[PDB]
Image (cartoon, rainbow over all chains, first blue to last red; front, side):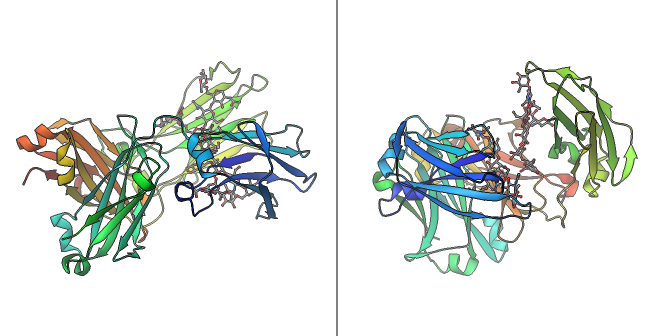
Length: 206
Length: 208
Ligand SMILES: *[C@@H]1O[C@H](CO[C@@H]2O[C@@H](C)[C@@H](O)[C@@H](O)[C@@H]2O)[C@@H](O[C@@H]2O[C@H](CO)[C@@H](O[C@@H]3O[C@H](CO[C@H]4O[C@H](CO)[C@@H](O)[C@H](O)[C@@H]4O[C@@H]4O[C@H](CO)[C@@H](O)[C@H](O)[C@H]4NC(C)=O)[C@@H](O)[C@H](O[C@H]4O[C@H](CO)[C@@H](O)[C@H](O)[C@@H]4O[C@@H]4O[C@H](CO)[C@@H](O)[C@H](O)[C@H]4NC(C)=O)[C@@H]3O)[C@H](O)[C@H]2NC(C)=O)[C@H](O)[C@H]1NC(C)=O
Ligand SMILES: *[C@@H]1O[C@H](CO[C@@H]2O[C@@H](C)[C@@H](O)[C@@H](O)[C@@H]2O)[C@@H](O[C@@H]2O[C@H](CO)[C@@H](O[C@@H]3O[C@H](CO[C@H]4O[C@H](CO)[C@@H](O[C@@H]5O[C@H](CO)[C@@H](O)[C@H](O)[C@H]5NC(C)=O)[C@H](O)[C@@H]4O)[C@@H](O)[C@H](O[C@H]4O[C@H](CO)[C@@H](O[C@@H]5O[C@H](CO)[C@@H](O)[C@H](O)[C@H]5NC(C)=O)[C@H](O)[C@@H]4O)[C@@H]3O)[C@H](O)[C@H]2NC(C)=O)[C@H](O)[C@H]1NC(C)=O
């Protein structure tokens, strides 16, 4: 049995209204000796907030067991380590994994909206570009909205390490050229721990 | 125990006849108990024997790492031929086969758009030059920046990202002194893709 530990989603940790969680997924759980125990420690201190989820089956006759631990927003943002100890007798080794936020000084993201190029106006749909650069850590959330209504036809590139040690990304919202030249205003909403109120908003219009 | 990893040719290699594209079959975790591994190569089923196997090099973890390199024809890879590397070892319950090929599907011509720096960014000393390449298929592509026929070499390119229409898009960002951009220098975004004429195109960008 091999374990894969996952971090909380960036949006969950930045808004107090949401609940961030650390996901500990055991993937090679076997029918024999399926007693997969879960002990959780924050900064080495055992905590009892976890809730193991029901198992799942696959096409390779292998079970999947997941334990979900709710985490405090500041605990993750302060860098505290989370250790997922998996106690299963399927294999002798008591596999243990640790997770933590990336260490280092958070750097404020820079948000620049870029209008579509003149060459793209030939096409029936144009591309609205949102450039976010100079942020650290890579944990970030980017969304698009217009008139207080979220847009859905956007894709965000994964964060990429830059020369200066910071991260950058692009978010591309694709809309009909009619909407663009009708004068509609679109906004790129960026959430990051180094932002004031963990949120900034840049607008783009004709 | 032994593990096999198959690597595709670099996108620039397959797109230029001048360069030599190749497929690398890397075997790790080769113990001294059975240090001899066999590389058998197949191309769409037919067994080929122009592969050059490198001598077994032992690593510091008492594990051997053997590598075989198969030179592939540019047209063969672009016609979707499948390259299979069969690795045989006496410490293996069964010989391990790995297959690599160009992403199956219909090629899509990339659209190249150069985007000027934001006016808000002009307050800085370094400005960002953006090259949007979208609507291409498959993933294999190369993006480079140059000015005055000389590589800029101060740019970072995002990975290809699967768009909603099934194609791929990416952004390449070139960081340049705000003095150079305002000085009037013209920079060009070079994109190499199989669905491009001569597998090459250039879109330029300058203060307008
Ligand atoms: C003993 O040591 C050796 C190495 O020794 C070395 O030298 C000695 C002297 C010491 O100093 C060592 O410290 C030193 O490391 C160990 O060999 C390693 O073994 C591991 C696995 O156990 C391999 O990991 C894999 O890596 C590949 C990528 O490898 C490229 O990038 C590496 C960057 O570090 C580079 O080192 C590699 O050489 C290789 O680089 C490429 O080389 C080719 C050669 O021609 C070149 O053309 C390329 O340009 C070049 N690229 C770059 C960027 O430089 C990685 O792909 C593997 O991940 C896949 O597999 C995982 C499961 O194995 C899986 O979890 C991943 O998600 C991923 O899964 C795959 O994903 C793809 C795409 O999504 C998908 O299509 C596949 O289906 C999927 N496959 C699956 C799921 O199976 C993996 O991480 C190391 O590369 C290897 N190091 C080497 C070969 O140098 C050896 O393991 C040690 N002994 C023991 C017992 O562990
Ligand atoms: C029986 O079948 C099961 C079902 O899976 C089948 O097989 C799969 C291959 C798929 O084809 C699937 O469709 C099939 O149904 C098997 O379970 C799977 O087993 C494999 C192999 O063990 C696991 O593969 C790993 O995946 C890791 C990523 O997780 C993936 O799954 C999750 C859940 O679906 C995806 O989504 C994530 O979900 C989280 C909640 O659980 C959520 O919180 C998170 O936000 C979300 N993320 C995203 C992006 O959506 C996720 O996207 C993946 O798809 C992957 O990381 C593994 O590769 C890496 O492994 C390590 C760990 O990252 C990495 O090394 C690390 O690098 C770091 C630097 O980057 C270092 O800092 C670390 O120190 C270092 N750690 C080390 C070295 O230990 C490696 O370099 C490598 O890159 C790996 O690919 C599957 O997760 C698992 N589950 C599923 C659903 O597929 C089962 O194994 C089978 N039985 C047997 C016996 O094999």
